Amino acid sequence: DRPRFSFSIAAREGKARTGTIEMKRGVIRTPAFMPVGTAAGADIILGNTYHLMLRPGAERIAKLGGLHSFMGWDRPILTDSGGYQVMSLSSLTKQSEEGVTFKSHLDGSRHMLSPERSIEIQHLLGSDIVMAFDECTPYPATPSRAASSMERSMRWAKRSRDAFDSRKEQAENAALFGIQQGSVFENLRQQSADALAEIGFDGYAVGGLAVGEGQDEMFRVLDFSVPMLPDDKPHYLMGVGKPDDIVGAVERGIDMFDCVLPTRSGRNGQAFTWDGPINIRNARFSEDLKPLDSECHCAVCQKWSRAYIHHLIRAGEILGAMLMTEHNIAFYQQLMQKIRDSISEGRFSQFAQDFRARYFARNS
Amino acid sequence: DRPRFSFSIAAREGKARTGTIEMKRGVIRTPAFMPVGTAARATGADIILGNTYHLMLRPGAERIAKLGGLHSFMGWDRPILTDSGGYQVMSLSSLTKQSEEGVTFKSHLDGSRHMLSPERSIEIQHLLGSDIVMAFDECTPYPATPSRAASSMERSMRWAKRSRDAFDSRKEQAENAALFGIQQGSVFENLRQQSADALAEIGFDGYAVGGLAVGEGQDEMFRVLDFSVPMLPDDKPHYLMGVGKPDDIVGAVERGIDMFDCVLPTRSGRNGQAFTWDGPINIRNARFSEDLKPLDSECHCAVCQKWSRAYIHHLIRAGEILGAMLMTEHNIAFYQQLMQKIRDSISEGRFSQFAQDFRARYFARNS
Ligand SMILES: CNc1nc2c(CC[C@H]3O[C@H](OC)[C@H](OC)[C@@H](OC)[C@@H]3OC)c3nc(N)[nH]c(=O)c3cc2[nH]1
Ligand SMILES: CNc1nc2c(CC[C@H]3O[C@H](OC)[C@H](OC)[C@@H](OC)[C@@H]3OC)c3nc(N)[nH]c(=O)c3cc2[nH]1
Ligand SMILES: [Zn+2]
Ligand SMILES: [Zn+2]
């Protein structure tokens, strides 16, 4: 009944788009924020493949029914390829054209990542959207280093395509995304996009960003990089990001987002609100009887005041960071919905202006 | 078959004791460290703990009861101890209305309101299916004037009697669980003696030393334990709430403590601190980026058989939450290994030597 992977765009404004990705396990409304999944509202959740590879192991995840039964989640699941850990854990890796081997453990165990093995692991995880095994080029990088890195990733992208297509069950029920690299350099971005389009992918991710370059540099790279990708295919900005990062990226053609800030902020005493992020540990909140956000519809905001959460956190009650995290996750979905609504109305440019004016005034 | 609650002392050295607490759900080897339980062997604990105040608010004591109590909630058939809320009475006092009846918390944005009292606290701990129940007390804030410490301790002692009666009013709880009284009095010796006498007049299966590990410092805490622990019944377990660092545990055992709890193993593991026999290490230090050794060369835990300092250092630097999970899993296991070496050394008559050796190696910091 449902298609394997059908991306439809229902409304546009400037470079921004809103629409749906239809898959066998459900519909993904775009622009989308995709939260990190955990072991047992968003349309799709994510699995940290490298993490699951080590704990409890991809084969064990497979034997217990894949990530859908592992996370109690019957809707789509996207998995990364490991290309980010290829960089972020590079000091523990031996890297070559064949792939990436990690340092042997104290028990003899050894893990390796390659275009073939990464697609095999993501298949074992039962993921619905598979990412090519790439390398997230570190920042900053010389044009020479960015070029060799991107070019290797593109050869890895072709191997990921073949490895995905070599498995009948995976090729007929999942989808494959290519990942554009090239650091901040326009000619290399164009090379990667062309190389990805020559191979063919269901969706196209903009990789190698949100690695310390700053929002101004990131927006500048998206300005020329997103229009290099196929316009009739989803655009996924990996690792992004702050709410204002999300809004500006949507302005530049991104349909899919992921990042760990909702949980990382909630564990560090930071809550996202329509008036900007607040540091709940600040003394101004010690007697603030308002919820974290006066408009938020999440469960936390219907029950918990800033004062209560501020004292929970000051008192060492871990429940306080859990409520902050639960609010931040829900706030992110509320942001994406308002984005989708405003594009559908033809008022996205006005929403982005109003969002920024209120988010940066910080009248919390 | 098994008794409700039987504490046996198998060996002693100075004020230190090792032995067993026997309960219907299993044996607790003492001195014991009791880790925080969550929702579902040399590193294994005999009893785990429930944050009653947390569970009261999420998901609720009644809901925990309907799903089979904390034993099925945490997938744990061995004993479970629950706190009473007396610490949150202090730590969240700015959100409370306190009176002789009990402690009422600030109403929520949904109309909901939570209150704690000696009667309701024992009722909640019963609903949680707890095996060891703590009296509803008040952990007196530090510092405190002698006047404030006195009114606080005396209120807690009246609450302790109400906790006893409320515990005894429920036949199933009274026949299958155990009740601990909590000594207060801040750092003041005369008040500690009043609290002990008052608790022993009432009668409890075990006696906790409350109101410590609240910022007084190890030197002050040891000074209070010097006179406070011998005020308690010698043939009953002694539980030091909130303690603590490994060197706090060793010194407390030297002064007669049989039971410990604290969140430092998880709090340290989430902040990049691992406990080792050479003292704590900050895994984030660059010295560990290529350190091929495990966190600790002697540790028998699962992490130390597989994971090097170098790998965990880079996991944490790379933002991989798995790094903090391994640090945490090692810290929890090291804690049980410390308690075992403590129990072994008392049984051998060598605890005083172990304590000297432990401190010499732990503080030299030759990691
Ligand atoms: C922060 N800036 C950021 N993160 C990039 C991730 C990783 C995304 C990944 O980020 C965490 O893993 C580490 C998340 O795990 C907690 C994953 O969610 C499960 C998430 O995978 C979708 C990239 N992944 C690949 N394969 N390639 C990239 O170029 C790339 C760029 C990123 N920038
Ligand atoms: C840090 N110094 C510390 N913690 C004291 C706790 C609470 C222990 C409690 O500490 C966390 O709750 C807050 C733990 O939850 C995460 C509880 O374990 C589940 C644990 O309950 C046994 C005390 N509790 C009572 N009832 N009375 C006390 O006098 C007392 C003294 C403490 N000192
Ligand atoms: Zn909220
Ligand atoms: Zn270990």
Image (spheres, coloured by chain):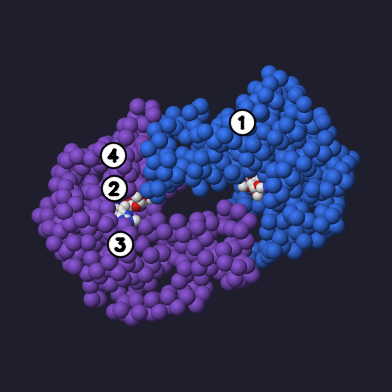
Chain colours: A blue, B purple
Residue under label 1, please give it.
Answer: A357
Horizontal and vertical percent for residue A140?
Answer: 75, 55
Where disc 2 sits, the SS reads helix
Instruction: Indicate if the residue with disc 3 has its beta carbon within 8 Å of ligand 2.
Output: no
Residues flagged by tags 4 and 1 on a common chain? no
Amino acid of disc 1: Ala
Q: Is residue B276 visible?
A: yes
Q: CA distance from mark 2 to mark 4?
A: 9 Å
Residue under label 3, please give it.
Answer: B216
Whether tag 4 and tag 1 are in contact, CB under 8 A, the answer is no
Task: Pick whichever of labels 3 and 4 is earlier in the sequence.
Answer: 4
**Residue A359 position by quadrant:** top right
Instruction: Indicate if the residue with disc 2 has its beta carbon within 8 Å of ligand 2.
Output: yes
Amino acid of disc 4: Thr
Residues flagged by tags 3 and 2 on a common chain? yes
Q: Name the disc covering residue B96, or none.
A: 4
